[PDB]
Image 1 (cartoon, rainbow, N blue to C red):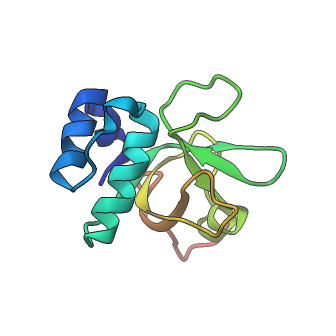
Image 2 (image 1 turned 45 degrees about the horizontal axis):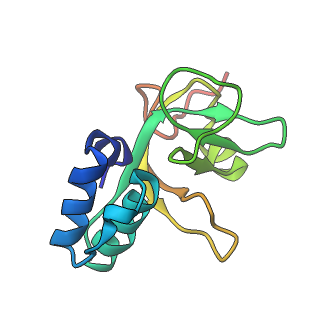
Length: 130
């Protein structure tokens, strides 16, 4: 579901949510990995999961979505964001965005943005040129 919502669930509430999905014995798991599990099990079950916040660009040409503070680096529960994604809808660091998420390939480690639902209080496109 919404990653920020997952974090809104205390580690114990995240393990009880996994138990509801069959993931039991998570008491030994940290809120980070337990959320990643709720993403794999609610997705397997076919539920939708999405991320949201304010993007952060990286000199490397890719960036991550997350809260509004900075910290300079990313975070484990943040969101991965490719350039084609930023470039494709004309985004910017600090931009406000919301969307669905999906895992890339074995080189996943962080989930990646997948579909855009909202961006800079505007649609992911336009038609005036400037």
